[PDB]
Image 1 (cartoon, rainbow over the protein chains, first blue to last red):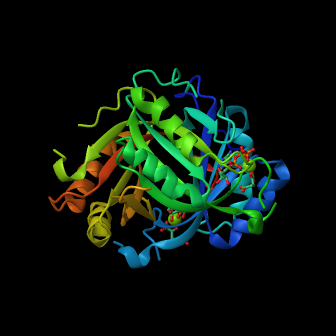
Image 2: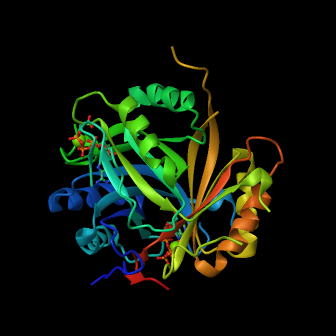
Image 3: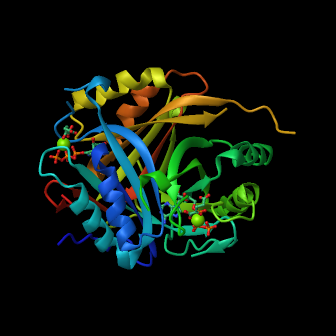
Length: 115
Length: 111
Length: 109
Ligand SMILES: Nc1ncnc2c1ncn2[C@@H]1O[C@H](COP(=O)(O)OP(=O)(O)OP(=O)(O)O)[C@@H](O)[C@H]1O
Ligand SMILES: Nc1ncnc2c1ncn2[C@@H]1O[C@H](COP(=O)(O)OP(=O)(O)OP(=O)(O)O)[C@@H](O)[C@H]1O
Ligand SMILES: O=C(O)CCC(=O)C(=O)O
Ligand SMILES: O=C(O)CCC(=O)C(=O)O
Ligand SMILES: [Mg+2]
Ligand SMILES: [Mg+2]
């Protein structure tokens, strides 16, 4: 099981899960998150390369990907990374990468509610 | 709004990322520009919050994102500015996230 | 010499550069030739009765690297995205907690 190392971020309450994967898997990934009860997410189309350099490389070799950013509590990181990795997986190069980033604060605009 | 940055001692810069209704973008940008905040970066995005949209990809709602990097001391004020201008009073107004930043470099004058 | 000392223990960092779109091919070429192991591109807009505003297209690169590579990569990006006129953009360095490769479940490294 995926175990994310958050030890260099003691006291951080919230993390951002940034998942970049094949565009055709977006509905699967979203269904898996919806079923788990995910409390929100943001989707952006991006382009990129990993270790294999696309397709040296140039802009023409960058490959279309879908990105999701999912801010979750610390306690939910591993579960959510695991769900997104499992849903996005095919077993071939280019299946994606997940970056976990620390978040200092969350503020709901409608209410001014923080934390 | 008070922002808890105690977990990041010694961090000098933060990124304020606001995701909000597209129609409020000109209001948010005007309020920030008038207050003297620069370096705004805008990306259109699609999303859901706690109510699960308008769930599947067709329930994702268009939103506008604005990212601004400020110093630690400026976070609370800039967060408040953004919140006040994005506000409408209805669910779906948006969220603001604050993120630590290690370093800032201006390309035109990089050493 | 990027000051990463408020991030003890953090292994990976994200280099985020926002710059003129016409410089994209050259930035990519430079990083490719130098041997970069990954990047992500996003188009974004800079913000240049309501006051007079203008949205200006820019290109964004996010490049996650190990600590040791941060200064070299920042230097190459700065040099390739430079024109010397006002409006060249900015580079930020952000801490990253974890990196997971989906195909393999491999983390870290
Ligand atoms: N170091 C990195 N920095 C920023 N973005 C990255 C990086 N590595 C990968 N990405 C992004 O994630 C996408 C998917 O990467 P990819 O799945 O090809 O990873 P990889 O490490 O090459 O693994 P694999 O060997 O399975 O292909 C890339 O197209 C790019 O958008
Ligand atoms: N946990 C999250 N992770 C990442 N993005 C999110 C998260 N929650 C909200 N967002 C982004 O912010 C947008 C606005 O969220 P919204 O304002 O609906 O927040 P909410 O917590 O549901 O507040 P409210 O009850 O006022 O609707 C979303 O459409 C999405 O793009
Ligand atoms: O993204 C792909 O579909 C293949 C290319 C790849 O894995 C890479 O550039 O790392
Ligand atoms: O974004 C909206 O307009 C309403 C939907 C919502 O608030 C949500 O999904 O959380
Ligand atoms: Mg790859
Ligand atoms: Mg909502």
